[PDB]
Length: 448
Image (tube, rainbow, N blue to C red; front, top):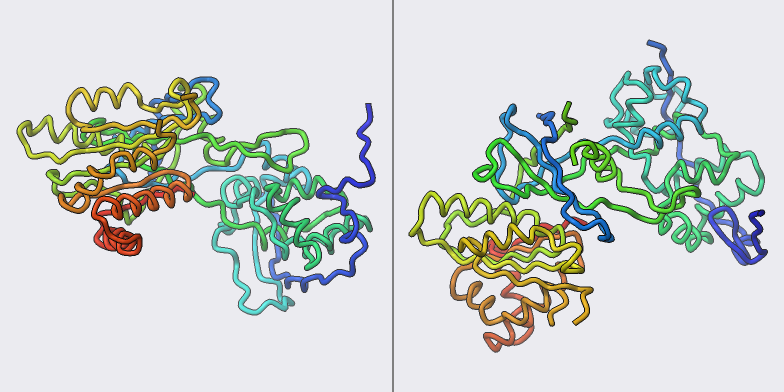
């Protein structure tokens, strides 16, 4: 059976009218500046000691808990801290890209970089994220975000290395004024990366120097500390969903995130310890109050629960040291899709409640058939207690998780709560929350 495409079908490689017949306003070509020669020749490395799948096998998103052994380091952390993980690109992706650039057989050559004597770029400097003299393999694996969506100026540069007339034309369309919609749809929304484009435009043969002028730094990914060193001394836990998304890939439907895809591969045999390189974030503010008598409210749907597991572990240990202490209330608003699939830490939370560490637990299930569906609905149902904690009892509220929408939804809920509870106008309520934030009693750790 043949792949047969009808005349009306547009795609990354094919426009339809009007764009296909349009006069193009094409951006100016970026001035090349890099000269490449291929020469033949406070970071902590910590083992992964444990990994646990927290979700059922049929959960739409797979959530993992990973334990790192920090015992042979001088690394320290407090609950709510974040740290950065240094991750590589997929070996298969790096191989495919080097193969496509006809560079696979030079993968062990050292990349020596200079500025071209004859460049028309002012202020041209060597990219700081490409270590001078490292192997091509090393640079593609560890230094370059090969997943990055090519900008219009990168597409513009690739026009000049594309020999097929229709393919060159399509790339002109994709970087032009007139091709804005097609770029947004077929490149940006589609999450297309360089390899995807080069496979889609087989006649595009760009030089390595051009890639190194456009591919950005491969950034480390931060994770939140999901444990207390009081509770698991010498260990550090973190929790993450494996990211999976639809892309331009022709032979694969879902692509995994760079860091979470790698972590999942690393821990397969632990689920000869695998090791990863991490480093602390110098500033961290998402912390328990110094005064343990102060009541707190934690709002952490899905994996946003992560730092709060660390807060609760910390308080368990603090309480063990000092029974009879004046310890403030601890409220958790947790949300997930299905009680029977992704109710993270269900047993541990039960433990915290049983022992009087967690004062109140309010869990919402957004996809179970019927009741509060999201954390914001449950917060509203307990508005009186929430208002009193924040406004009469000097309390703090913490909101963590991947959605910025979640953060806005929680915010708007609190606005409604303060208006109704104190009986002030929506505007005074909004300014109260802003003053709460200014005083560091309303804290956010938002992940996207």
